Structure formats: C-alpha cells, structure tokens
Length: 370
Image 1 (cartoon, rainbow, N blue to C red):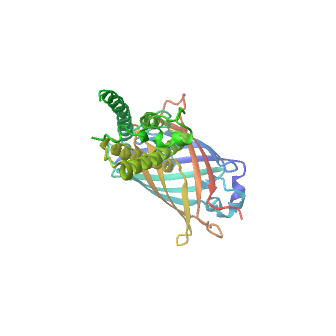
Image 2: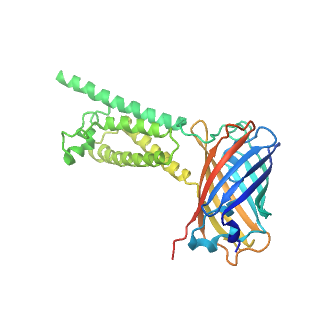
Image 3: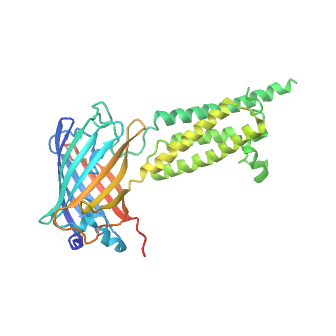
C-alpha cells in the first residue's frame, strides 16, 4: 500500500494554529519518524511567545502513521494505507472538571516531508485551572502524593502508633490486678496466622500495627514516585493490606464482636487506598483503542490520558478521535485493535524560547498471530 513510504526515516513537519479561551498561539515542530522501529523524535517551539497551555496537553494533537504494526497486523494499518494522499484526523478532548479542545488536522505527504497541519480551539476552560493556570507537571520524577493520599496514610500511621501505645498501657494496668477485646487479642500479632505457619518466634510475627507503620509509610512514599514499578508495587501492597483487612474484619465481626472505631477506620482507609492504587495502574497505561468507521470510510478511537498535576492529583483527558481519508483508503478497514504509546518529554538547555523535546514509541497490538 503506502507502507513503501515509511521504510527508513521520514522527515516530519508539524504546524498548529490554536485558540484557547481567546488566547491565540501557534506551535511549530520539526523532527524525524522511523516507522520501522515505531520511533518518533521531534522538537516543538511556540512561535508566538509563552505557550498559554501546558505542553503535555498538546502531545496527542502534535501523526499515528509512524506506529510499528507487527508483520501479522500490516493490513490493519489504515494510517499508512491512507498515504500519500493523507487523512483528516479530528478530535474532541474533554478535560475532566475543565474545558475542551476541538482539533481538525490534515496529515499528508508534502514532498519528502510528512506534514501535520492542525487547527485547535479550546472552550470553557477556567483560567484558574490546571491548564490555563500551568499547574501540571512537565516530565517529572519526584512529586507530591496529594492531600487525599497524605491524609489517608498519615491517618493510618497515627492509628498504628496509637494501637501500639494502647497495647503498652493495658500491659501496665494489668500488673496492678471501648475497643478493648481488640487491644489485648492474640489476633493483634501476626494476624493470628503467622504463629501457626512460620512459628511464634519468627520476626515476621510482628504486631499488626507494625506492618501498619511499614504499610502506610510505604504507600505514602510510593505515592511520590511516578514510575511504573511504583504503581504496581503500590497495587500489590494495597492488595495484601486488603486481604489482611478483610480477614481481621472477619475477626472483629463474627469472632470478637468488638466494633472498634480505630479498627473500622483502618478498614475504610485500606479500602480507599486499594481504590486509589487501582486507579493509578489503570491511568498509566496510555493505550489508544481503535475501531473502524464504515460510514465515513475511516476509523474512530476512544481513550483517556492522565496528566499529573503538581499538587498530587491527576487531570483526566477524554479523547474521541475520527480519521477520514482524503483520496483512497485501505481495501479493508482495520479490526478492533490498540496502540501502545510511550512518551518522553525533555528540554533543550540551549533553547531560549518556550519549547518541548518529544521522544515517542508507538506499537500496535490487540490482534494475536493466527
């Protein structure tokens, strides 16, 4: 088809004309695309001055024809099949609790250069928000855990240390001849299970409250990292804590019958942390979901993008996408499948103007080999 055009490397020119809440701006980027490896390298600069919106909010609008489709999925590459005539890609980007982007781009060959010409208009953005307020995170490693997580983990830790204290106190008061069955209960060490498995003398047979200190400290720390292993580790830890919490709840109700406010609160915190940890792993996977549009003879796509805010929360971005060819498309439109995209934003220590260096790796999946 048009795959012959994407062997080797292809130059890339991107021009965006944007208007967000009356703020008019233009962006220009140049780079190279290697569809053989699914690799994309581009440098963008704002030719009109300071950019009125954080750079990560434009990564998606600022050329999916360079995606690496495995050999067995070649016939599902509508993008490359649409060349060199090109296609028209429109997108509606709804920012949760904020405004909207509407984009119409023409992607086509102009000689040797792949050209993406974009018109973008955002409406109903609140100028105090994370977008027009520049409250997002450019590429970043250490960050804040958010007031929700900080509160949950600080609370859990305080209740842990408190549990230890109460144990200590009853210990003394006994020697002189609420929530009291729980605070002198052999369940409160090793979950009443370690002593039966590893033996009483083991060092793993610690007070539930100690595993609590380590658990909430770990959750708060991993809350500060942005890597993948931090999200997954957070998920597994939250899982262990959830199992132990459901068990100890089977011990509170159904065994001890002590409706302790401390312990119950613990349960609520562990459920919450489980939910958040669950969300994180979902959000990090930046995959794009692609279906075929017979009425328009093109394709549609739905997906959500997570943008890390500087205060610890996450701005969600819902993405509706359409692509209609300009000349003649694939003899068959692609079956359902998705595009995994890994982005890396960086800066140029020599660039005096508002800019963004973008590296990107896109691969195709969703269709196993027959």
